Every structure is written in C-alpha cells, then in structure tokens.
Length: 306
Image 1 (spheres, rainbow, N blue to C red):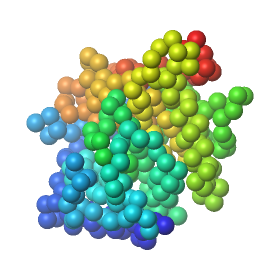
Image 2: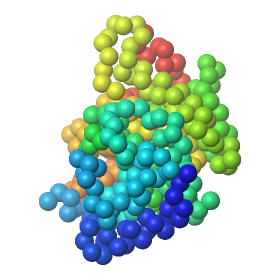
Image 3: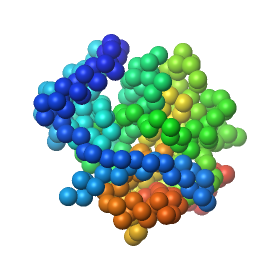
C-alpha cells in the first residue's frame, strides 16, 4: 500500500533538502516545439550549466520513504541534481539489475504512485530505462517519476484519445503512430483506476514487451541475439514501450536520449543546439530514429526478420 500523503511528503522533503544543500537544482528553461512534417509536439528544456552506486548509501535527507509499500520492495529517493523539481527515483530496496524486466508488482506500485500524486490537476510520468542503449546511467534497478509540463500534449495522448483500453491479439496490434520515425508500442489504459489491477498492467507490459523484443531476438535464427534495451513509459492514460538501438544520437545534436525523449521531452545542454532545433524541430524526430528502430506500424512482428 502506498505511503499516505506521498505528494506532500515528496514536496516537503524536496523543499527542505533544497534549503540546506542536500540537493541542488540545475537551472533550466523550456519551450514547446512542433514538428512541421510529423506534427508531433515536443518539449525542449535548455540547461547550459550542464555542459560545464548512489542508491547504495543514499543520503537520508533525500529518502522520501524507506519502503514505498509495506514490503521491503521499494524506497523513494529524491534526485540529488534534478532539472525537474521533485523528480524522484523508485529504487529497489535490495540490489537488482536495471537490465531486468519490470515485475507485476513494479507496475502496480508505479501506477499507484501516479494515482497518489495526481490527487485521486497535475500530470505525472513514470519511466524505466532498461539496458545499455536506453540512457540508463546506473545498474541498480530504479524507476523514475516526474511531473510533466503543464501544457504539453505528448503524441501518445492523441494516439490513445477516445480509444478504450484493450489488449493486442492477432487481429488487434498495440497502437503505434505512423507519422513518427521510430518503433513504439502503446496501449491505452482504462479511464478509471477501478478498472486497473496488477494483471491488467502485467498483460499490457508483456504484450508490449513481445513486440519490443523482436528487434533483439530472431525467431528464424538467421541472426544471433542482440542485447536488449528499451524504454518503458507509464502515465495514467496509457503505457508504452520503445525498443532502443543507441543511447546517444548521431551527428547534428548527439543528444543523450532516455525514456522522456520518446514522449517528446528533450534535454539540451548548449545554445547552438537549442537554436538548431528551434529552426528545425524535425531534428528531434530524426534523433529519435537514430536512437531507436524505424517505425513498424501496420506490420506483424513475425515478419520483421523474415
């Protein structure tokens, strides 16, 4: 069960630690962009000062909760050097590898945290960077939770809008936006948290995973396995998985891309890059392709390697 008054606890732990120097906020400014070609909305954050096992012994002043549930599964830590204020890490109490899949209780715990923070009108995102190409910096398993920008509408939203929860089958594949350059898989989630339980979440994740895995494992055995990497993104309205080829993008930007990139949130460290993207928002779409695999919308996962 999720700690009571989690949101106030996060807030209060955060202001206190900013106050006395247990965390320092990196200054940043953000703005909206729109891909003229693909229509996809982006949120670009600019943090110049950035160009100039923490979970083992985390600073107690940063620990919002020792166990997010009754179980010794999870602790909730504040990010020590956040761009987004109150940005938090759900860390496995005991060590596990970040290359491991999300369990069912992982999913239910993350969804419950979202519900708790969202007041049941701010929006929260929960995400997981799995593997070397995901943008994962650390090997100790953790999820991340952060508030999404107030007016930002990620493409997943429009993708899922007015589309009821379902699960994939041979007739119905996960939603994927064809306008975007990159492979991704999304299921809408029920509007009401009463329709959401562990098993629904688990089945959502497994079926998304099976699509994501086809870029790594090959059923024809005409290729040897690759190393698995993917982003999981979870909000209250949908869940999404992105297979990842490279942690960092190619020549013009060379952005480090994590989960947030794939709902369209980009972090840039220098003003030349910031103006490149302003002039040409379509660069983001190109970067997302370099870091992922090309869009598979309208295809059976089975025919990828065949």
